Image 1 (cartoon, helix red, strand yellow):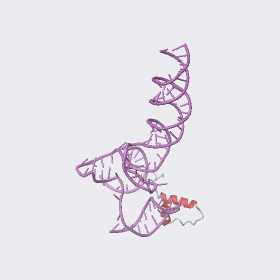
Image 2: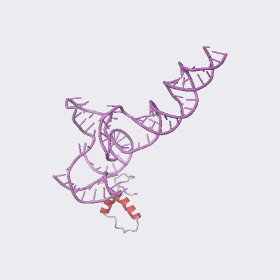
Image 3: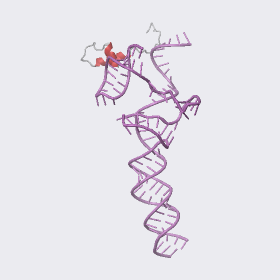
Image 4: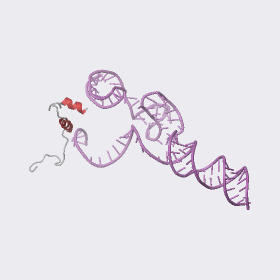
Amino acid sequence: EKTHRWNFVEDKKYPCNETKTMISSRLDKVENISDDFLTRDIEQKIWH
RNA sequence: GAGAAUGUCGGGGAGCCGAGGUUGUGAAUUGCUUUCAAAAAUUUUGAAAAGCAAUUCACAAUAAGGAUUAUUCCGUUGUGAAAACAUUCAAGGCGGGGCAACUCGCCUU
């Protein structure tokens, strides 16, 4: 921060694909599975 | 000026529910008034009936009304003479959801 800025409200936060983030955090809490189960199709199915 | 994304503040419409209140029916108790109808000294006491109620409980209706048997409803909104409308509105197919009814998406006319 001491040397740059990013053209946007310097104290504002912007959504960055929160959906898959939540799905992934909760699908990581589940454990006892491979770290590849969350694919695009499975993500869409969970969201639906 | 237009659009897309992200926040803030407001506005509108629709929907699933809840608690009273009011009026009326019945009951428990206590009253006011009138009349009967006795007893007693125009006045006092007692039974019955009617009017008006109070406190509490169960129940019925809650815009007059009109449908219907679906676990459905229309009745205080706007336009305007057509007493006619708006506020529901096609067809398929490929899927998700469930105990299933039913609910949420995708594809082409």
